[PDB]
Image: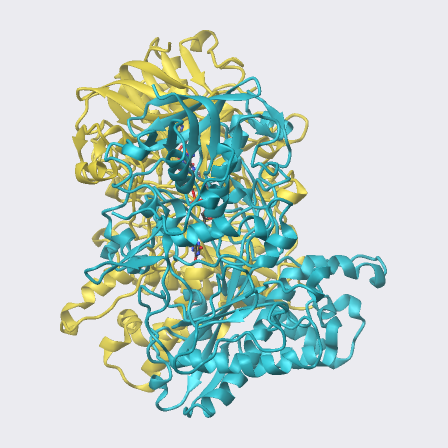
Chain colours: A cyan, B yellow
Amino acid sequence: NLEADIVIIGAGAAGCVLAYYLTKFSDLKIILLEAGHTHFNDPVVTDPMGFFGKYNPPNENIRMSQNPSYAWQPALEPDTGAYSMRNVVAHGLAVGGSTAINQLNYIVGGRTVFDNDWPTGWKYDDIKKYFRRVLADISPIRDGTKVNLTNTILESMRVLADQQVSSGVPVDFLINKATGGLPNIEQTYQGAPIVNLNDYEGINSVCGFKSYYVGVNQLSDGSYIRKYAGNTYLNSYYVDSNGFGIGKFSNLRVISDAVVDRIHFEGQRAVSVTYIDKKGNLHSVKVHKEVEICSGSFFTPTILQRSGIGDFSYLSSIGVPDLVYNNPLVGQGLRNHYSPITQVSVTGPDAAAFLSNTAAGPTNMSFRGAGMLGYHKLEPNKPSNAGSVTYRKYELLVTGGVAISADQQYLSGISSSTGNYFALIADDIRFAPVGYIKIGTPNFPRDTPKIFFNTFVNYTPTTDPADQQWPVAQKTLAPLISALLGYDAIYQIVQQMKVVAVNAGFNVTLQMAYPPNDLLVELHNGLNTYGINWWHYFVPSLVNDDTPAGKLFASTLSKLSYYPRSGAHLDSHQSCSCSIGGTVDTELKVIGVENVRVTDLSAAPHPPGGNTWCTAAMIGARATDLILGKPLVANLPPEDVPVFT
Amino acid sequence: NLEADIVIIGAGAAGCVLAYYLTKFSDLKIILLEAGHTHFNDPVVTDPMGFFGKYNPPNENIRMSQNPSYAWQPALEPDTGAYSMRNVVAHGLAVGGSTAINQLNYIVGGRTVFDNDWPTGWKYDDIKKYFRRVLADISPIRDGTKVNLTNTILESMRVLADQQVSSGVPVDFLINKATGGLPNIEQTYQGAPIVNLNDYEGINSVCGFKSYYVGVNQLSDGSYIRKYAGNTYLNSYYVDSNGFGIGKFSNLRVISDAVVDRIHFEGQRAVSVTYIDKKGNLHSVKVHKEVEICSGSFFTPTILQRSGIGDFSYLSSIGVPDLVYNNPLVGQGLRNHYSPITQVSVTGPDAAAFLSNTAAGPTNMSFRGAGMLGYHKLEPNKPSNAGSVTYRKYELLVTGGVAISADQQYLSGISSSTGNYFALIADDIRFAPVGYIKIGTPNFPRDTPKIFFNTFVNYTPTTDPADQQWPVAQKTLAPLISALLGYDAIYQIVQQMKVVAVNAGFNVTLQMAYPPNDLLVELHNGLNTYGINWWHYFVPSLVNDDTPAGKLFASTLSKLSYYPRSGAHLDSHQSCSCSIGGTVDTELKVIGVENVRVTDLSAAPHPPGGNTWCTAAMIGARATDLILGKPLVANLPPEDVPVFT
Ligand SMILES: Cc1cc2nc3c(=O)[nH]c(=O)nc-3n(C[C@H](O)[C@H](O)[C@H](O)COP(=O)(O)OP(=O)(O)OC[C@H]3O[C@@H](n4cnc5c(N)ncnc54)[C@H](O)[C@@H]3O)c2cc1C
Ligand SMILES: Cc1cc2nc3c(=O)[nH]c(=O)nc-3n(C[C@H](O)[C@H](O)[C@H](O)COP(=O)(O)OP(=O)(O)OC[C@H]3O[C@@H](n4cnc5c(N)ncnc54)[C@H](O)[C@@H]3O)c2cc1C
């Protein structure tokens, strides 16, 4: 028997903060159901480099996100825009959730995304305190090793940002309007100050820096360890070995291996929750006040639909007997990021000194920069505010070795063994495609529901006059346009690096080796010779430009369209399944019911400006104050932090 | 309350026969738990062409094996031999199991596989009656439309089989030793008799025919319908709408949507089985005599391991509390088939007449032949009996259109729109690789367990002398050798077709367009100039043949090794997870327990000579007589068949 008045389902990035700070500041009885044990002893979780497979057995060399004993394994339906490939993108299965298996990065997101895309009450000035709270809770660190490649790249970026600042055009990709004429590029010399990307006031929307902030901490011995939600908020100092709380937190219960099925639900009010344990028995817990769903973006709409909230026609079709509320918007608007990869060759006799000091330590995890960039000059899909507000579009990442898939490694002829290649990535942060989630069987939580997500689709013309069917091709082709413009933005960095490396003491040469170089120079020339309407040549049957130059450009675009489909990576930043306004109101309460709330990343109405870990924790932190009634977390002094064991 | 003395889990190809003929011939109380409703009204299941997506909604065009509401969706761990790609291969989820979503083909398997690879009591003369039983139960039909391409191919096969019969070599791929000197190729002219591939006496181990036997039946209206296990054995004539039996079968209960978890198991004797229904409640059923597991190859070891039979150390590690029997061989020896694809171009002005009468009707489903072939002359991995017994190695299939993946369609430049291309496939029936299955969470039946299956791995040499490390490279390279020899066997058919099409009234030319033609002629020349030790050049660091010709051959082999990895298809013929001798004895009884048996395809000790649907039904049929005690099914007259509603 386990009656309690707050029941949280899932201890992820948001569940842990919620439980911890909700039992600290009140006397209600909190229950946390997670379905996964605590990996506080596993060397593959505590050690940061275990992310790269240092402790893997020889015969089962698979990463944690491919291990069914560490992660939920959802595979999406064939991708009609990527040659119908199905992708498996995972969720963490442990205390701490996906933060137990992630890359440990802290992009906070810009100021402008919250100011312009989130509803009132969620503007940036209303949430910055919670971001400060989560950052102070973790205390990330910076890179502990310098490298001259970062120097060369930073000089190149400032060199071309100088000419972008002039020329008067307003929406180039290195223009930050909160700083003014001077470029927002970190200085590169002895004793240079560090431009902080997650700054408090949100000044830096577009900036170039030399290091990220990764969530690890150094021990007195010398070893580094992971610092995740389950490490800080539910550790042996705050919770017993039996799951009971201790002292201040004695009003807290955590059940370890408890897979939750649905919400037994009297009238339109929640009254009980059932789950299954490792024994195989079914248990019921009684609810007095509130149910919180923090089960992740893929599996929150699933449990909501199984309970009875969703589309009545479909749910009746598959066989859900108990219907509650007819909201056909549950599980809509799924969003994600997407990172295409380019890689560059260095030609010379003694390039080793140029690529030295790049191996992955636990303080950077192979990230060496390099910045956040805004919209390209020639992208037609921009918000109207772009003239007066700087948005975040691309996240630039530089890494050693090759990062393409193994099949592409064979096909392109470039191998990971050689030592004159390095990778650049322009991750898309405002990715356009939208998908959705539905369940297929109303029995128990299934590992694979129906997930639909099509990215790089094409446009099939009609007999409509060309003048009035361009502005549907624009929307249908947005992602391909953005990926190609990212290719161009990376390409026009490398000759700047040529100049900088020449005048910094290096006899080296840099060229883009993947995709093929000529295929990129042709894109550069096509862009600068066709202007703002360059993208019309994606559909060659409407341009009516039958000249051989136009045919060349169209063929180049068609050939380039292959690379982002196959030689890229879909990220694991799922969100917005049950966003604000769609499924829940500003108070995180589900429409059509009076005592259930959803507070994980699946409630965000727009993805943040980068990696989506701070946002989920912030949502949980604000849910704490929403539930209790008055702001206690928002006013805690920053010197009060959870101690670590 | 549902006590009964026989409880079957899963109504697949073997569960339906077992339940039907076990309640017909006895008075025990039979219960069948399936976890899936009856699709007797769904047009996408009853109509054969619904397999190809005739009734699919426009926005969700996915086949039945990719639909989570029709199939279990297991994805295997990254394939170290295929550029680390994860493949999703499904199981049927309905009455009838995988036969509700399959291709409807009836390869029975040869005589020699059962005579040489299965234990005593399971030789061919001990089982042929049950194969006749299942075939008479279904009554498949042959192709209802002729085509001249089959004529040309059959002439070509007999032409080269004539010269293979001479030349005295004993193990070519068109030699059948049960017929003698004359070729075993169907005659090709007016009123020719039909050589039956599933013949009663098992004479035809290697034969060339013009049609397969697909499991459909024609109605009086004119429409064809699917004829599967759930259609024949559990239909409205034998089982009520409520799941009760009727009259003769009144001693039978079928529960529709019941997902089974584990076996509650007193002492070392089975006493109860628990399941979950669509309501979300957990039910228990009492067992008096027997439990049958017919849950498929992927999910039978899963339920056995969750119950408590398996490896104690690992099961304790993941958290199974109740341990029963320590058999570390549960879930070992997983086998499957594998089909690489080649495709051929026809060059000429009026090839349309040559490729006419090839569209897929419900009586062939785009299969137009062409035979079963034995070992190639130059394969080193052959059983010792191969001199005196003919084994089945390849299954040859001919089809219209292109059958490669969409990515390969783009890369190779060949498109499905054009009308001068057709596909050939040499499916490997004695596929060498072996994998295994383990569970990752002891809570509930998960859709994705750990499945390990690596196919086309490479050999890394050591400092061991070359003379005494060849016979480990042979075993490690068996699958690649077999695939390449299949490529060669297909290639040396097309010039025979050149001659036959010339002398049959056609001005057409045939050449292998995928893989590239020169890459195949070089393989042909390398084979005939390097002899039986041609495969030594897979590892170029040991041959010590530094001549440029040897370098050419090694490069050709390395380039050809890419095609079977990416341009092929893994089949859905899983088997042998709990085979005879490994997990169960000759009586299908699980070792370490006295009242549980497993009777689905996961009990086969060696895959059959072709498509694995007749074998599963045969196993169920023999289990019927094993359970009752005396042969009632083995002596039923062939004119007694289940009527159809
Ligand atoms: C491969 C990978 C890489 C990542 N890289 C980064 C990165 O570079 N930067 C970054 O900032 N973030 C990264 N992340 C993390 C990710 O971006 C966010 O942290 C994530 O969205 C956190 O959201 P969440 O806490 O709401 O969900 P989760 O953390 O996934 O919470 C899910 C929790 O709910 C539980 N649960 C689910 N279903 C049930 C059920 N039926 N019953 C009971 N419990 C249930 C699960 O066990 C788990 O504890 C990565 C994640 C992965 C997997
Ligand atoms: C895509 C595809 C193509 C195929 N093509 C061919 C072909 O060309 N030729 C051919 O001969 N065969 C074909 N097959 C069929 C296949 O080769 C065999 O018929 C199959 O191995 C049948 O084995 P089975 O009956 O033991 O397993 P299944 O038929 O898969 O039986 C599984 C049954 O167990 C049930 N079950 C599983 N787990 C549970 C659980 N926990 N609780 C309750 N019930 C459970 C499932 O609901 C299902 O009813 C194809 C199958 C597929 C999927």
Q: Nearer the viewer, residue A318 or B364?
A: A318
Q: Is residue A150 above or below residue B446?
A: below
Coordinates of residue B263 in the picture (x, y in percent): 29, 23
Coordinates of residue B539 in the picture (x, y in percent): 28, 72
Q: Is residue B494 above or below residue B590?
A: below
For ligand 2, give the image quadrant: top left
Residue at x-position 61% and y-position 36%? A585
Residue at x-position 30% and y-position 42%? B437
For residue B403, which quarter of the picture?
bottom right
Q: Is residue A85 left or right of residue B457?
A: right
For residue B254, which quarter of the picture?
top left
Coordinates of residue B499 in the picture (x, y in percent): 54, 67
Q: Nearer the viewer, residue A46 or A251?
A: A251
Residue at x-position 84% and y-position 57%? A464
- On the question of residue B424 being in view, the answer is yes
- On the question of residue B427 being in view, the answer is no
For residue A259, which quarter of the picture?
top left
Q: Nearer the viewer, residue A437 or A174?
A: A174
